Amino acid sequence: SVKSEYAEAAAVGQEAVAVFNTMKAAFQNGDKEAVAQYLARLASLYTRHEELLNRILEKARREGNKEAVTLMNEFTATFQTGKSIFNAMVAAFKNGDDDSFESYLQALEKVTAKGETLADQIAKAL
Ligand SMILES: Nc1nc2ccc(F)cc2s1
């Protein structure tokens, strides 16, 4: 069902949270080789999550589930805020700008924490 598809999407999201926290530790410790690998792993994970979310939103639209579509439209918009901040983090890493990397990382954390009550509301609406 769309609901089990959202549970699968949510797990992929939690995998990115786990890898992100590991990456943040590696950044603080200065292990740039690890950070590079974790950033590649996060890119693939966000690419997967985004696509799953899109399929869920498209299915909610085909089902006529207006509330779930509203919530998912908002949530995907927020996801793209996170995506832009993540990409800016990756560029800061490439450029060696640790000040910007720290900034973007904290902003990604706050964007993620904010969009959590919505994430739960979607599970209930689908
Ligand atoms: N809370 C979030 N972080 C990211 C990071 C990258 C991305 F593409 C989407 C999101 S949503």
Image (cartoon, rainbow, N blue to C red):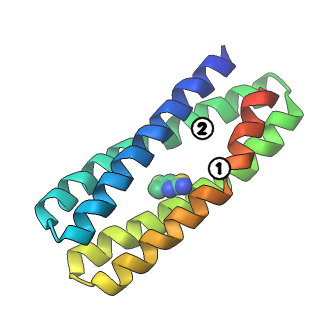
Q: How many marks?
A: 2
Query: Compared with residue 8, is residue 70 higher up or lower down, i.e. above or below?
Result: below
The extreme top residue here reads 1
Query: Compared with residue 119, is residue 106 higher up or lower down, i.e. above or below?
Result: below
Question: Is residue 5 visible from the viewing direction of this image?
Answer: yes
Q: Which residue is mark 1?
A: 76
Q: Earlier in the sequence, mark 1 or mark 2?
A: 2
Q: Residue at x 87, y 36 (%)?
A: 67
In the rendered image, residue 101, in percent from the top left (x then y), is placed at 35, 77
In the rendered image, residue 116, in percent from the top left (x then y), is placed at 66, 49
The extreme left residue here reads 33
Q: Disc 2 residue type?
A: Asn
Q: Quadrant of residue 88?
A: bottom left
In the image, 24 versus 82, the foreground residue is 24
Q: Which residue is mark 2?
A: 54
Q: Is mark 2 within 8 Å of ligand 1?
A: no
**Which quadrant of the figure contains the C terminus?**
top right
Q: Residue at x 38, y 42 (%)?
A: 45
Q: Quadrant of residue 105?
A: bottom left
Q: Disc 1 residue type?
A: Thr
